[PDB]
Image (cartoon, rainbow, N blue to C red; front, top):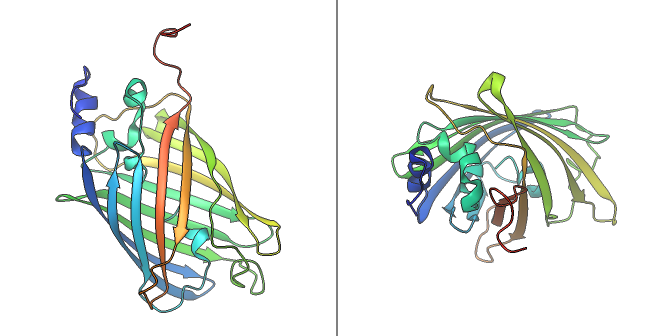
Length: 243
């Protein structure tokens, strides 16, 4: 909805009332393997709900789809009404923000990504460049030894006033088919594209849940993604309203 005492919050929340179309474009290069991914779907910030179908437009994806879940739109996260003054992602809109990441896979290579997330008219667009180096050929990544699922996880978000944005470091535990886990340490920084003011948040975390599925009628290498992202970690406003 729109009814917020803060006009800055009302500016951001209004852009994400209801369902918004999403376009995702990634151009990636992992160990010389060049690939491109196009994703389409819709986000519902009211419920923190994402529905996206990604298509590898260059053939077979040289990396497992779970390794690209976080790389392949945080502005659709559901921030509770008492935490909406900490929604950096919606405040940077419609100009958008740059999302840069370095993803270290334990005992394997690393991803280096840079994305520009912004509105193209009514459509929320995520344009991504990916560069992967030093990956082991027979490893869990290029060997496609990971399971096709995603574990739920909480990730803390912290402000970065020197860059007028946010920063985040967190661990992703991919499930290997033999029962083990492939650690993927994420380092993230976000900076607004426009020079206007943004909402610098307090330290809070995002609860994330993802379901991976397949379109039975799709013959191209693809991934169907249902993702829920809800912010938490800030108790009400003053004290408590019930105890």
